Amino acid sequence: GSFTVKKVLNNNVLIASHHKYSEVVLIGKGIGFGKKQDDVIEDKGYDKMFILKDEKEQKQFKKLLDYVDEKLVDISNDVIYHISNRTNHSLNEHIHIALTDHIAFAIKRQQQGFDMKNPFLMETQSLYPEEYQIAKEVIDMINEKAGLCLPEGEIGFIALHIHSALTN
């Protein structure tokens, strides 16, 4: 429904007041831009908005903002939005914490020239062919958005996070 801004964390992240005075974390493309406390926002529907209701998930997401920039928050939101649409399933809130941290790690690892090898891509794809396919499309998205080429081994890791988000 309608949300009231408590604090803007960055251009893509918001602390908001909601249902029965619940405090939530809002993540979306440009949701926080030019916003200030007491501003009333409604879901635009076109900015890939996600809500973090769980108190422990909100705490963990806000703590990761101490190092992950707004751009990386936005790349990860774009991939989670794609995962959500491709699975046509409810993803647990933790994907916003675990996967954002994982994407930022993988990008920085590649930027620093640290090569990586995943020896189990064949077994990951065999056990999770749908999650593996979505992960390949997710890697293509990250590569375009961050302007680099993530190692192939990362398809395996993304697929396993997708399984976890779908199952808890």
Image (spheres, rainbow, N blue to C red):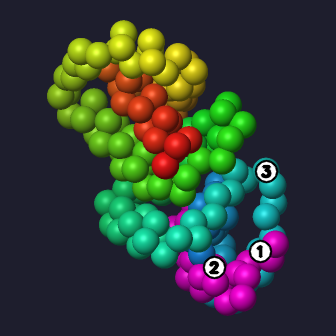
Question: What's under tag 2, amino acid-wise?
Answer: Ala
Looking at the image, which is closer to me, 67 or 59?
59
Q: Is residue 129 left or right of residue 158?
A: right
Q: Earlier in the sequence, mark 2 or mark 1?
A: 2
Q: Which residues are magenta?
A: 1-23
Examine the rendering and report whether any part of residue 30 can be seen.
no
- Residue 100 location, x and y as percent? 43, 49
Assign a secondary structure to mark 1: strand
Q: Earlier in the sequence, mark 3 or mark 2?
A: 2
- What is the spatial separation of the Cα atoms under label 3 and label 1, in whole angstroms? 13 Å
Looking at the image, which is closer to me, 104 or 128?
128
Q: Is residue 13 magenta?
A: yes
- Residue 39 location, x and y as percent? 73, 83
Q: Residue furthest left?
A: 114
Residue in view at x 22 percent, y 23 percent: 116
Q: Is residue 151 magenta?
A: no
User: Viewer-nearest of labels 2 and 1?
Assistant: 2
Q: Which residue is mark 3?
A: 46
- What is the spatial separation of the Cα atoms under label 2 and label 1, in whole angstroms? 9 Å
- Residue 54 location, x and y as percent? 53, 71
- Up the image or down, 77 lies above or below 70; here it is above
Magenta: predominant secondary structure element? strand
Assign a secondary structure to mark 2: strand
Question: What's under tag 1, amino acid-wise?
Answer: Ile
Q: Is residue 123 left or right of residue 88?
A: left
Assign a secondary structure to mark 3: loop
Res 41 label = 1
Looking at the image, which is closer to me, 57 or 105?
57
Q: Which residue is mark 2?
A: 16
- What is the spatial separation of the Cα atoms under label 3 and label 2, in whole angstroms? 19 Å
